[PDB]
Amino acid sequence: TLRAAVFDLDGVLALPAVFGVLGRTEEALALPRGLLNDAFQKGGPEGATTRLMKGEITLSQWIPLMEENCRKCSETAKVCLPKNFSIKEIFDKAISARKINRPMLQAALMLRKKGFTTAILTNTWLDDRAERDGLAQLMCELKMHFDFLIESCQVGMVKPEPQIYKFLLDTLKASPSEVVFLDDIGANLKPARDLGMVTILVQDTDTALKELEKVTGIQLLNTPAPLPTSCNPSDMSHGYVTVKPRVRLHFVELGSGPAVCLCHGFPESWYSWRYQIPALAQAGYRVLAMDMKGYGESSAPPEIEEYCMEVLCKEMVTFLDKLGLSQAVFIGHDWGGMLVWYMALFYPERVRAVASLNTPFIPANPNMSPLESIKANPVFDYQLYFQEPGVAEAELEQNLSRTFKSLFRASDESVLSMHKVCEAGGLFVNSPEEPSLSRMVTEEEIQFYVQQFKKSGFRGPLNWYRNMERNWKWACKSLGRKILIPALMVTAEKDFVLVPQMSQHMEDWIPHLKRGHIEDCGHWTQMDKPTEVNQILIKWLDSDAR
Amino acid sequence: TLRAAVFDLDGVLALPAVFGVLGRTEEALALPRGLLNDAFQKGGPEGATTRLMKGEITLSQWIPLMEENCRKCSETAKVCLPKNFSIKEIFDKAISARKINRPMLQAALMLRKKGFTTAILTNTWLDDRAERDGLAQLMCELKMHFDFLIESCQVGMVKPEPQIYKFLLDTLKASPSEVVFLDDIGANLKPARDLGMVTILVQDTDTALKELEKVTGIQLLNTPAPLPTSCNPSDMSHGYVTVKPRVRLHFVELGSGPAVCLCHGFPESWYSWRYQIPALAQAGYRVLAMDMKGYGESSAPPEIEEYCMEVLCKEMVTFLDKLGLSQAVFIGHDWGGMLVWYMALFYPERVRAVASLNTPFIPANPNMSPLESIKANPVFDYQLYFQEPGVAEAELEQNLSRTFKSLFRASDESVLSMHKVCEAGGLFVNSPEEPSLSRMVTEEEIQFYVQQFKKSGFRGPLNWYRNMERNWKWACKSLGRKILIPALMVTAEKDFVLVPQMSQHMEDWIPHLKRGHIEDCGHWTQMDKPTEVNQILIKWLDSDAR
């Protein structure tokens, strides 16, 4: 019964194989067949390339040794190397072209999900070229999906020496019979086979995957498109900034590049962006996912007026000042989306670009209080229930597990009616005490939210709804303005509270507004349609905020 | 007795005054005198510009209103505006040219140091231009040096309306008689004077500063060059990353741009980089100043082998992986400098550039143990005293205040002999029990270190010295390599432990090595010569790591 799978990097997880570029270079330059491959292997175990793979010398020290090897090989073949011959140019282009073999990585992720331990065993070098960042980025993307990464140049051993396979089995804590080994080079399989390992010679990916399926008993080919990579909270960098004496904000950070601030809604957490954080960082952005004021590890003062938009926006500006960021792209959802439109209206100099998921920009009505406007819409009755301090808190804190299981559901799985909440006496008065787990979340994901809300409670979160008149008064100062910076509005078809029709007149205030629309998507946009959200945000960021 | 000073931004703290660019534009374009200034003030309190300064409209909404004003003014003057006339091009260039008036900012910093409360009171706009980041960066640099920043467009009031001066006095909690008010516009002084404030009309900076000196009694002009801006620990963003089950690393973060990791020495803290962190962030870098393993808020496991270079470097790579950084510039001092040379030797792909303060790169000697090498130099006798677990800890933890006051001294203030430490029985056996405070540090700065070392103790820090044989064995694997990435070595003339002569053969291993040398500088380089360190690092970063 197999329990571990070992993959090679070159020719298996990354294509095209850098070793195969020498074959295509000889053809293009009309050089004798196998000339560059001979210079590459020249010397065997004592040759320059073996020393490179063992970590004795770096890639830049090896380039002039391979150049000499090319000249010595050409003199024996009775041929001359071209005028523009450069080993550095050949290897720079070969390393740059190599992309991740997606079906192979997907098969490794599936095996790991099914309980297998996965590893990369590769003959690689210490890259000190001016272009070494390209290799570093590739290694980082692959690294997070594997339990172990054993690089020849770090252990001082190379394939096919039998000692590297013994070191591998020692690291894996497994017998050779429980290990599948995938390599594109025949010579590298012989030692794994001599020990008794199941070996797969990888020539083309699909045949290698059919062999892997047959030997593991798991379907790898023709399987559905997987969900985006999620966050493990304990693997994140956690940041803490004091913006005022009693107020500290917690955030999670990943990536480098332009700052992108993610602002969650009610009653959520930074964890609601778990599918976006790795994708946006991989796209080349530095992601800061906040615990908004009143939530998780951020401060939760009890005073209502501590959660009016004016105070909230001012603290967000101070957050940027203390981090030393002159600007950030602001992306919000639900209450966070309401906040990012007001950041664009009051502090445009600090906002690189503004994006809102579900929440439309609706300008304040000076002739009508927001309270009277809430009576006009029966779906907004739950907001009147949230007004009296203590009432909605007691119901929502009564059983946290029930609260989050009833709220976090796909549009067709809904168990709550947002109408006559006040008349019914509560939000959950007509709901089951033990709701079923939605297909959108796992029990482990639900438990993260109950842990976060055990410390804080719902007072801070509910206070965001208890400043309607103060927010209205403050918003009325911006009625003469327009939003003229890059802006994106994303509507969710099945959000029956923040319906797409509420955003139809936004172009009057934000004339160059860009749009996104997600079909069959409810209120919890990020966890309902994570792949679609990532695609719409990355496309917009790369064009409007870069 | 004056206790508050209020400064205007345009024409006072930032020059040239954006209002004065209209005068130079009329001259250059041969337009009638005062034509552009008339279009600018057209309408008075009800005109486009007053609405812009009140925050009613944004800068981009105001540009077409000023354009129309320019055309209406030209028709009355019987003149025609040029073919290439653009208000946007004029204002873009005017805002871009405006730099900080250094002598004025220095005078404000001096007044604040002498107990004054300082504020900026300015008529400004909501900038939504594609170039608004330039204004945002300027505002951020000025912001941190003032107690209050009151912007017209945020309060809905403008100078010279008397209500803005009443709002100012309310914010300052001071009587008009205790306030100095500096403005370049005569009209803006009249209301401050009517209330009884001391006013200074700023035409040229030096005369305004002579008036400010005469009225405050403090010398502002001809005063020495001030020290760089330092960090207040409670104003920093604190980050925490778990790199392995028992190991968490703390770091402080500021700025945006390429990642720069600062690694302190023994027995220090992230706080040792207090003068570099704001300067490097202002230069356009994202600074991560670590508490190295064993120090401050980072984990301090008791095991000796938890502090060997191999383990330390591996955890630093994991630190980059968890933050989502493919590369960082590594800058070290003392033990941190020793670590950054080994990061360059073993992980070149993760290191953008490497810099060391005081610590030279000395390659391992395979024919001689590091223990025998330490006997050959009498100044390295203190390292043999640090070997036995428990001995140096008891002396260093006995009185923390004495430990840091005896260690942190300028080269001429030394109170310790590094020779015959073992024979004498200790490091402080011939030292005063109550040493005087060095001119290099304040009592408050010393107390930060005693607070940090109260939690940790000296076991983790001293364990960095207790892996000589293991580090030697590991370093011997890199003897065939060279450092071929951008590298900087900075020597300190008066460091009598890490003398500049110890770095003389570094070019054999790092052929393209750049150098820096600081005269009259002891061991504590960062706090001894902060301005010189900042200048050498920023110059090198901008050319080699950008």
Image (cartoon, coloured by chain):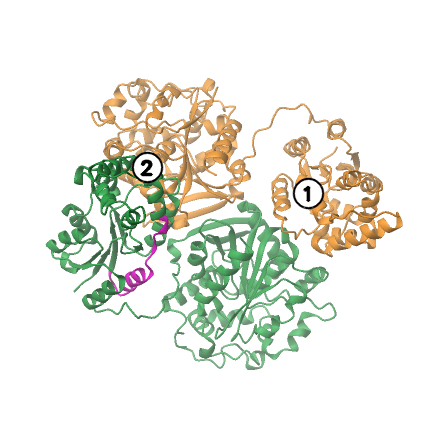
Chain colours: A green, B orange
Q: Residues within 10 Å of mark 1 (few under 14, many from 20)?
A: few
Observer-nearest of B151 and B546: B546
Q: Nearer the viewer, mark 2 or mark 1?
A: 2
Which residue corresponds to the image point at 55% horizontal and 72% vertical from the top-left? A391
Q: Residues within 10 Å of mark 2 (few under 14, many from 20)?
A: many
Q: Magenta span has A108?
A: yes
Q: Which mark is residue A60?
A: 2
What span is in magenta? A95-116
How many callouts does the rendering have? 2
For numbered disc 2, what is the local secondary structure? helix
Q: Amino acid at mark 1?
A: Lys
Q: Amino acid at mark 2?
A: Ser
Q: Quadrant of residue A88?
A: top left
Residue B347 visible to an observer of this rendering? no
| On screen, residue B89 above or below A367 | above
Residue B57 visible to an observer of this rendering? yes
Task: Give residue A178's position: percent from left, percent from top.
Answer: 16, 60
Observer-nearest of B489 and B38: B38
For numbered disc 1, what is the local secondary structure? helix
Q: Chain of mark 2?
A: A
Q: Chain of mark 1?
A: B
Task: Give residue B470's position: percent from left, percent from top.
Answer: 24, 34
The main secondary structure of the magenta stretch is: helix
Which residue corresponds to the image point at 77% horizontal and 49% vertical from the top-left? B158
Disc 2 from disc 1: Cα separation: 46 Å
Q: Quadrant of residue A72?
A: top left
Task: Give residue A204's position: percent from left, percent from top.
Answer: 25, 61
Which residue corresponds to the image point at 64% horizontal and 74% vertical from the top-left? A374
| On screen, residue A196 above or below A88 | below
User: Dot 1 corresponds to which residue?
Assistant: B93
Q: Magenta span has A406?
A: no
